[PDB]
Amino acid sequence: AVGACVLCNSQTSLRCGACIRRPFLCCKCCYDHVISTSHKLVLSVNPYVCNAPGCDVTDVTQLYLGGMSYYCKSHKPPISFPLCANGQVFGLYKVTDFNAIATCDWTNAGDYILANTCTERLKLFAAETLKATEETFKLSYGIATVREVLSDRELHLSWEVGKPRPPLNRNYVFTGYQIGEYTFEKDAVVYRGTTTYKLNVGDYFVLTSHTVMPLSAPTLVPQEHYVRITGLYPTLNISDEFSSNVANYQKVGMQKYSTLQGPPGTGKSHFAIGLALYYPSARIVYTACSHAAVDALCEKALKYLPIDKCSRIIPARARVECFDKFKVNSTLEQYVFCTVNALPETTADIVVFDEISMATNYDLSVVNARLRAKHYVYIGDPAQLPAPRTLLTKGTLEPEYFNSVCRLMKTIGPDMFLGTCRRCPAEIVDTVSALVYDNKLKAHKDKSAQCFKMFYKGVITHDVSSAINRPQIGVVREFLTRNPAWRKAVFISPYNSQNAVASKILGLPTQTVDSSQGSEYDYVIFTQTTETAHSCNVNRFNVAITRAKVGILCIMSDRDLYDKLQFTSLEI
Ligand SMILES: [Zn+2]
Ligand SMILES: [Zn+2]
Ligand SMILES: [Zn+2]
Image (cartoon, rainbow, N blue to C red):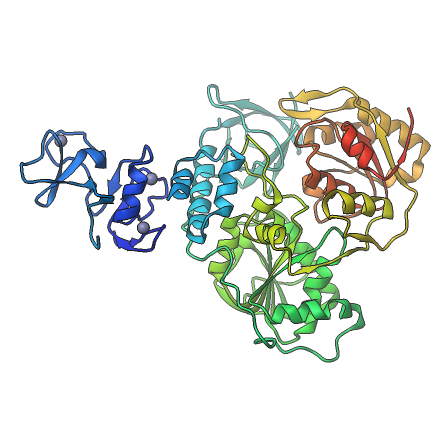
């Protein structure tokens, strides 16, 4: 029971027993915590509890030291000292922000604001606390027992009475019973098992509650600026393709860590892989939270880097299908592509952490704990989507609060900014440039004259909470008959239920705005579905319309975002 105080590092035997992460708090900070919060249980080798037989006094403010033991006011000997007095709690070696992190339920946006504006040790305490609170919350839901199986992809479920039913989307991942992880989509439901197994009737599914490990490494290592490129050896023969990023690559070797804000289609993966060609002998670990982000880096590496020096790290508990072209699980290869949770304990000359808007402070800390590098490059865009905060229900989380990296990019600016969008028609570039980039994003492409908008509120029905707009899908159906080139469009909306309906009525491939992030398609058809904070979110709107290379049709519910679209308006 010997450790360091999370607020002032002073050594102690005192841990707060009421905090779910039981942080070590010194004599001074333990007092400031117990006297200002409902937290009154203090722990050491032995807890601070009344030693008198059958006594239930556990409140440190109602306890005293009687020689070497602890007793309440009713049981203490005449010669006894209060454990709580004079701004200290008794212990060996003898905060407003800590109290709020320690006691919040993580349902308000203000809780996440604090977890990102506090000191570095409090950011780790906040990240550990939040993740443990998120995992304990998973236990609240009800079990689903297979009543009947229809085909190889569809079944019917029987839910536990009394306990709430979690939202059925590709976001919530169940664990089958250990018949592999399973996922659900909208009385006939669609079942998706990782391991192809003949769905046994009577078997049950439960959400994967994993143990939250403690955080040691900071979210960001301390910044170091150098006079020369350090520990990296540049090429003088650098491919003309990557010449645009030479000054940025030099900035990377002249700092401990660097931030790159890359709006959609501005060249983030090109930048990440070109960094390997610019420092040809440097061992680079490419990491991101999702398998899709890691795979998109693998695809770019396949095109420019020697395949024999690449390796895709895959966890033995193979969840989803990923990149199969590199040698699997070779930690020692020069180029290692791996998701944040599967990272081995290794070193590198450069660590590239991509899709930084999707990282949490927990992820930022894990990377710093498993990878010791000469340089760290954080690539992403705070104008794109963050990681879903399952507990957050009240208030909106602004980009400067996504994580420490996004906070830096939004306050002091990013170290490097990719200012030219090469993917999108100018109509889209001009719209998002004004909306989220302060007019700094420029279009490479001309206006395509294939970007349309329609203001159509339709009718909003709901599949539990997930929304559907059948009249908006009807407008799309009518448009498709008159615009056959759009037969190849990807249908996008903010809701899985809208997408399930569009899939059956239109037959187009479907994507939620959130799962479309990082991907691009020639034609995109977007139905806003509703006017909610979710469907009107500017970052979500930004991602939605920037998926299109050639054309986009936006069927809008919100007048504000409709008016902001620099698209040709359609009638009906
Ligand atoms: Zn302290
Ligand atoms: Zn506490
Ligand atoms: Zn007592």
